[PDB]
Amino acid sequence: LSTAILKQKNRPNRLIVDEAINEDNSVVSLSQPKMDELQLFRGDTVLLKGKKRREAVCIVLSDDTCSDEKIRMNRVVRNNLRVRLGDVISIQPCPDVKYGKRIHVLPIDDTVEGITGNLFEVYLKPYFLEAYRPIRKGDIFLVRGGMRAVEFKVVETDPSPYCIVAPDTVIHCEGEPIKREDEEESLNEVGYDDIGGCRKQLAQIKEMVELPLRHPALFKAIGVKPPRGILLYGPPGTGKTLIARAVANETGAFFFLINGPEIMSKLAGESESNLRKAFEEAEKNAPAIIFIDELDAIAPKREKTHGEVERRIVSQLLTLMDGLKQRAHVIVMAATN
Amino acid sequence: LSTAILKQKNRPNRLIVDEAINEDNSVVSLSQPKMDELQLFRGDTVLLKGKKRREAVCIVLSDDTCSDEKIRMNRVVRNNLRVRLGDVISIQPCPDVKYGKRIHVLPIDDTVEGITGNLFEVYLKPYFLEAYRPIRKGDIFLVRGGMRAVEFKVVETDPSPYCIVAPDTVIHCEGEPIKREDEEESLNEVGYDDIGGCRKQLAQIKEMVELPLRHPALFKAIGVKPPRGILLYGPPGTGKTLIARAVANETGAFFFLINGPEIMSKLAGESESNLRKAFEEAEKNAPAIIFIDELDAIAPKREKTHGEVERRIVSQLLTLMDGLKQRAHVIVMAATNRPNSIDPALRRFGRFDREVDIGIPDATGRLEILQIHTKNMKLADDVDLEQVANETHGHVGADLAALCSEAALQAIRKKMDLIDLEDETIDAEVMNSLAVTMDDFRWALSQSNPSALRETVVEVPQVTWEDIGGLEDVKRELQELVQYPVEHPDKFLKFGMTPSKGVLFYGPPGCGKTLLAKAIANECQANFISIKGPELLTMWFGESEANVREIFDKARQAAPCVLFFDELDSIAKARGGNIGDGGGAADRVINQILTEMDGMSTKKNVFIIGATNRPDIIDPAILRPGRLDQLIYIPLPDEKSRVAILKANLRKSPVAKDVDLEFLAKMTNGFSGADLTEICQRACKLAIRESIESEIRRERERQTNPSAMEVEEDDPVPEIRRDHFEEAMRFARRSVSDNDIRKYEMFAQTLQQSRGFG
Amino acid sequence: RPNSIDPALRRFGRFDREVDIGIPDATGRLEILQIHTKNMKLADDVDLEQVANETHGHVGADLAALCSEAALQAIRKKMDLIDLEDETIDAEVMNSLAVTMDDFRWALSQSNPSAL
Amino acid sequence: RETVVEVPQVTWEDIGGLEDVKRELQELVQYPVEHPDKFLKFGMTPSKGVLFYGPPGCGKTLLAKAIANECQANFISIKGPELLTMWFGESEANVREIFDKARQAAPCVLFFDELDSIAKARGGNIGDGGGAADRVINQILTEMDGMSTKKNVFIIGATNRPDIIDPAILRPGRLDQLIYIPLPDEKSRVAILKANLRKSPVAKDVDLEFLAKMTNGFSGADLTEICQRACK
Amino acid sequence: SIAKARGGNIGDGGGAADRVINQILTEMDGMSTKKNVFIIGATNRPDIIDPAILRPGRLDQLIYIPLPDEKSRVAILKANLRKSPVAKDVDLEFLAKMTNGFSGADLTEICQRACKLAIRESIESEIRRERERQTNPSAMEVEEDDPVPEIRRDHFEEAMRFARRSVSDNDIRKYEMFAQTLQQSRGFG
Ligand SMILES: Nc1ncnc2c1ncn2[C@@H]1O[C@H](COP(=O)(O)OP(=O)(O)OP(O)(O)=S)[C@@H](O)[C@H]1O
Ligand SMILES: Nc1ncnc2c1ncn2[C@@H]1O[C@H](COP(=O)(O)OP(=O)(O)OP(O)(O)=S)[C@@H](O)[C@H]1O
Ligand SMILES: Nc1ncnc2c1ncn2[C@@H]1O[C@H](COP(=O)(O)OP(=O)(O)OP(O)(O)=S)[C@@H](O)[C@H]1O
Ligand SMILES: Nc1ncnc2c1ncn2[C@@H]1O[C@H](COP(=O)(O)OP(=O)(O)OP(O)(O)=S)[C@@H](O)[C@H]1O
Ligand SMILES: [Mg+2]
Ligand SMILES: [Mg+2]
Ligand SMILES: [Mg+2]
Ligand SMILES: [Mg+2]
């Protein structure tokens, strides 16, 4: 039970992906007892949750040749949810529908180059007019209203979770296109599937960091105070900054990063201000995490320290660590070798 | 009388709480001779005093079914006075009644949410109009003028001690409500009931700090100047900041706090201003206390200090300490965990001359710390805290806190198939089905790595005389050497004899020398410091002079104690050599031991005992009058001594009636106590082998016919029957040869002659 | 610390004379005790020459702390009447304070001196 | 240049002979892990130490790896050459770091090895001005005393020069269970030669019994030398 | 201790001259005679002594202090026994005629043993009195005096039984041979 927190806990609302034969980019395949199970009436908009906090919404259909344990979707949704073939995806009935005021799509330029022509009346007309197709802020969808695959990206939108775009919602095309590198660099984010060989330690870090921030009521009920500092250590090259970025992309808390050399490279009296601003922004915001990377660059032993300014930075860090109270909901974790 | 200041001193005006059946929140229950005793007329307002300086006032009633020794009140007064069921509360007749001008209540928002409605005409009307109900500034009272329990809090009021609210007193409801966390955090303040394992030191701190501030007239009358500096010290984690906050919440003096890193983290020239403002605000105000926490961060030794600004901060602190005069009524107390890295100019007379040593707790202390920390957890009935308190050996208070936390997290992990990290909230039955069992405390105790394992243990031992077999003449001699100068001082003054201080035990290995030295300390109820030559050849090469002075200073501080040196052959054979070498018969460590043993005053009751099993390479300079004098040779045991040893080792395990110990001692000839313990341990291991093999045969037989599984057997072996001792007798080998025994006889007769030549 | 002073200050014309205040002997310790106990109210049992013989490595401030610890022991024996909880103490209790030889034996048992 | 803390891969099957010590090492190591309460029925506290000593080449390292493979425990290995190096630069930290790492990775067998190099660089050949107690082995004894029994750290030693050994190592509460590992017998030599020859294919014309009846004082290292010569 | 931590037992690589005793000789040379500082030494191992200590203008006047004679032993036993009161039944002359190679430390050991035996009898007698008063506490009417004020005799006989000799006779003839000729150690050997 030492690694029991890493179990996926399969439930009736768990849906495994599979290949879908519909070229429409708003389809799901659910069976009739599944729609009668979660009270999903025909035409509902569910809230799909994938990996690395990416989400998606699609209008539901009753594809009765689907199985009760799976779901079928195309490559567009599986790239908007960052899943492979054979990964679970939660479903949530969220019919809280409000319309949008203005949406703002943006194309990707390398497919627009070649021939552009007119973007609006050739590309944005036949896909949006009388379709009611839902979007999330940050989706990449494909319209075959041109020469070949020219993709669009919804960036600026006033409804932030999602919205069903009515035909009266104002559609623009005046903005600036996006590069291919801008998406392909953001497809190289880090999750828990990029860490190998450290299962037993990821169990401990999820028990120490994720659980006292999602459920403070348990620790208050059973009478436990959660820890305030975690120190990762190891040899050089063993993946400590990687586990840092993995928790930074999962956890659903506010994340703030402090580097050792970046603090110590600044002028005297500006580095203490950066430490104070870090802890003030973390206590001001949500349940938070502060990651201090390379701790032994900003706080060595005081037999090695010769300056006055470096002893002042160590004493500043001690004073800021003692200010964390049980009310604050701030975890500080640091890494060293 | 060393802890006589911690006595509660029961008086006729002492009232023990009890449960009251009146739902009214202004009732007390007093008997008629109590009201005729303190001249309490019916309808008086008394001044009730509880814990942590909380007070309360209630109008008195004559409830004659109450007892003369108790009082009865509800939960409202017992939460306004911070007492439990079975705690004393002083009463004071204070009829000094003046009315209030404006009062200002404030609700608590979590009970107001749900439905609020109109607060004033529904909540504040029927409880205040024509009631004359008294309040203290800071009370939490309950009015049933709504949906459920909606509590109010009186914050702003012009009469500060208390007041009887007339109906003409202006009542407001416009203010801001208070959160639940704002009260529940302030219910976690610290008193003297949150400190466990430090009774003897709390006595000293109340004699030094509370008494010269409450009653300066006594110290001026008898002619005593009270001290100005107290230095608490100890290992990390032993509760020094906790004792600080406890005095900060009791004492009834002005309290000011200074942190080490908070002073040293500021810019140059701003830290000296914070020190000066601290002492100016303390001398400006009342009888005060200044607590300087982590003193060794702002004043280290000036060989370590490299700055100019840090030497200026140390000199500023010395100048401010010398400005304290007898007129001022200011006590300065400081806390550190590195008591030898403080600048030595601060530890002189007039600055930080008193020192109180908070130490590592023993088993009785660990039980009290565990009972304090688990008062909010929900323990199962299986949990025995005395077993846990015995099994935690090198722990300090913070380690026991981390032990309780790790146990409850294990209890969560066993309940993981219901709790989801993915969801929003947890079922209330899952939050109610949490109870920590003894299996959790065994997990948490298996995982914990404590902090104070590499410290020296100063305790009273647990070995009685009964664990030792044989050696009865040396029991009669050691009683006469140790116990009578403690118990009968004057009988050495009738004659002209000064008692001796040293004993040396020497002999063959395994003969039982350590247990006697522990047993005499258990007999006299003295402390016991144990040193080993391996432990003293390590941590000398790094600190070349301090180690043996630290041992003798710690033994002088913890008097009366027996200071037991042991394993002297390792010093003698790492420095003096096997067949002799270029090194001396005198050894550097044993040299500094002789120097420390000479300068030891006889008014102390520190008694020194040695032990070696290589008496030939011993230093001659150890043996001289005024040092280790009383040579006692401890020999191999005789056969009745061997029967007594075998009766001694066999008390924990159950054996049968078929065994004969007399024949078993008549088989062994040169066998020590270690060899007889080896035989008993071999026999127990053979019995455990047979038990496990029998259980394997039973489980395989149940696997053979699992259709019935109907044996329902009992325990196949509860004891050792016989004949394991025969195989153990076959295994045994002798430890000391006979040539060595005649050599020990020849050193047994004449070792005192080794002083001169040879 | 007479050997940590800069040696240029101890030359001719600057700090050439030196007077060595030292650790007192038994005749000195008796005089220090008779000075410090001139305001205390001693019982008739107290023999200061025995105390002056039994204090071996003490200097003057140690004898001051010895007298203070003795009088605090005399307070602790009178503790069942004195209340920390109250406001003031009865004048007969402040008049019934007199330090006996048992107190000086307690205080002398507890003291750890400086110049051993 | 790091210390490897893993579960080893040597099974019992790689070792030939020495079956009584297999039955003894199971009883010393495996039962206090597997059956805690059966030591609470009686009043016995289990021991913590084993010393193996004997002639060279007899097969002492493989047993210590094999018991760790049997119990599924970690395995830290130390050599006296490795501990006389990186002591002269860090005079006190090294042996504390080893025992702290073994306490952190519990349950593990902590295998000291090659004690003759410490004993012969400090204690000497025919004796000298140095002691029978050695500074490194002194700090080892200090670290071995202050070790709590709630942990399941088990200590195993090995030397092939048992005369210059420190007497202070051997005392109850330290390395107790002395086991002498002898030269192998002829059926033990047949088992050793069956053990070394499993990786390489050999024919049916070979006789191992005669080949063990030729060797008299030959250890396992010598029989492995013979097999390696044949493959070359 | 200086001679045996630096000069050694049977000799070693160290010298007969020792570093501390070297600096002592240097300080003893540069000492003006107008001062009245007088230096006295003591050792009980006269063989490994530095030869350089003994030279004119340094520690000159060698005095060998021997084992005491029997009238010297009577004087020693009169000296140790002045603090404690003893009786008139004791004979010190026979008690010195029993001891042969016994020093002053041994005679002080005998006297200390006798005082310890007397204190044992005193405490055991008080325990019997308190238990007898516990037996019949209804009266409690003895009002006894002091059962033992002095040492009577016969504790010295048990103390005589305990005693062991401190210096053997081989050592005494070795000290005689160093007593006659120690000044000749300056040259060779
Ligand atoms: N467990 C691992 N799984 C996958 N990739 C890893 C793992 N450990 C290291 N890597 C790779 O190693 C690269 C460097 O790892 P880092 O996280 O930079 O190491 P580090 O922990 O930061 O060590 P230092 O002290 O900062 S040099 C990462 O970018 C990964 O590509
Ligand atoms: N005697 C004790 N009784 C009850 N709780 C204790 C005791 N000693 C320590 N604790 C607990 O240990 C926690 C930490 O103790 P601290 O007071 O922080 O130790 P400390 O004395 O400050 O040591 P340092 O030098 O400051 S790290 C406290 O919050 C208590 O929970
Ligand atoms: N008289 C005795 N009664 C009971 N147990 C004894 C007795 N004598 C020895 N022992 C046992 O002998 C073992 C070692 O005891 P110790 O006194 O520590 O031995 P030692 O005299 O110190 O010699 P070493 O060098 O430690 S083996 C323990 O198991 C004791 O229980
Ligand atoms: N019983 C055995 N079974 C298999 N191989 C063995 C056996 N005994 C020894 N060997 C071989 O002997 C060689 C050395 O093994 P080790 O146990 O390391 O020797 P050792 O006892 O440590 O003595 P040294 O000092 O290292 S040569 C290896 O090649 C082993 O395969
Ligand atoms: Mg990194
Ligand atoms: Mg603290
Ligand atoms: Mg011992
Ligand atoms: Mg090997």
Image: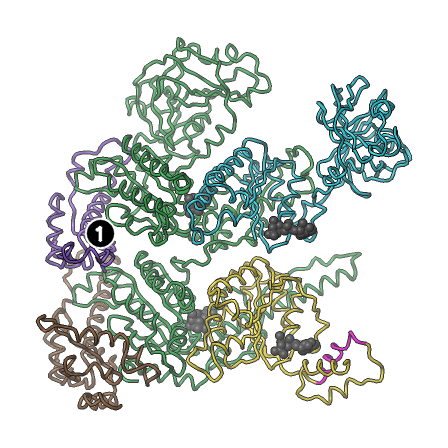
Chain colours: A cyan, B green, C purple, D yellow, E brown
Residue B63 left/right relative to D214: left
What's the magenta region? D186-200
Q: Does residue A163 lie above or below A262 as drawn? A: above
List the residue tagged with mark 1: C107
Say which residue appears at 67% left-offset and 45% top-offset: A5
Q: Is mark 1 within 8 Å of ligand 2?
A: no
Task: Identify the image quadrant of residue E43.
Answer: bottom left
Residue with the most extreme left position: E34
The answer to which of A224 and E131 lies nearer the viewer is A224
User: In which quadrant will I find the C terminus of chain D?
Assistant: bottom right
Residue A214 left/right relative to B339: right
Classify mark 1: helix, strand or loop: helix
Q: Does residue B30 lie above or below E114 as drawn? A: above
Three-letter code, disc 1? Ala
Q: Does residue C10 lie above or below E184 as drawn? A: above
Residue A26: horizontal and vertical position, in percent?
84, 30
